[PDB]
Length: 99
Length: 99
Ligand SMILES: CC(C)CN(C[C@@H](O)[C@H](Cc1ccccc1)NC(=O)O[C@H]1CCOC1)S(=O)(=O)c1ccc(N)cc1
Ligand SMILES: [Cl-]
Image 1 (cartoon, each protein chain N blue to C red):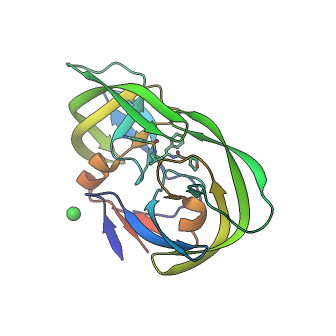
Image 2: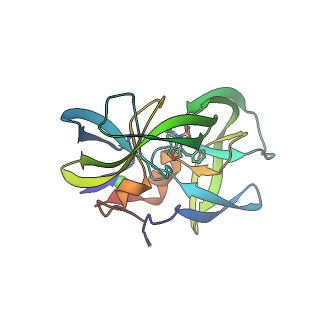
Image 3: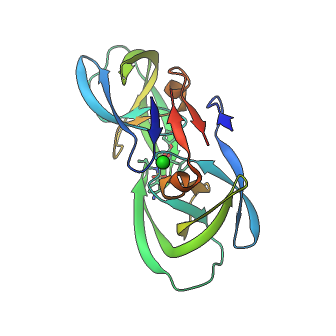
């Protein structure tokens, strides 16, 4: 699908059995999802941006269905205002920025 | 061009006669650049990032060249980790997300 940017590029995703809305973000290195429970071991990490840093839990090898496309990779779970799909998963679904 | 996301989508921008590096950021509503001197009066603006809200200076009708493409629009100046080209200017250069 070809997504224009007149508005936030939001899509529906499936993770850990729940349905959520997330932003397709080329500016985000890794994917970050709001507080939720995920299975497995995790390790703490700090990610920073506009406003500073937040502490997140790094879960590896998580499966996510992005707009009907399955993908595997690291997911950061923490107090983010919005669910963000980063480059680590955008690449897996073959997303590109065109102009 | 067609930009894959295996690495940060960085591009050269030309603003105020200077060459700078900037990130094509679909998850950013506005364009935010590091401290520098811009012409005209500014208005105050509050923007929200991953770590909270910050105060920036808004300059309108600034001429900016993004990867060789000329745009003219709003540019915010403040304490940002990297120069960010947000949706306000991406729409001007006709950028889309495809997959
Ligand atoms: C600042 C860039 C370099 C990185 N951020 C991505 C950006 O797309 C970020 C996404 C976002 C949108 C709305 C609320 C909160 C975050 N937009 C952003 O700050 O929008 C501001 C600037 C203009 O409009 C509002 S990040 O969230 O800090 C980040 C850092 C590390 C990881 N692993 C993932 C995400
Ligand atoms: Cl590829």
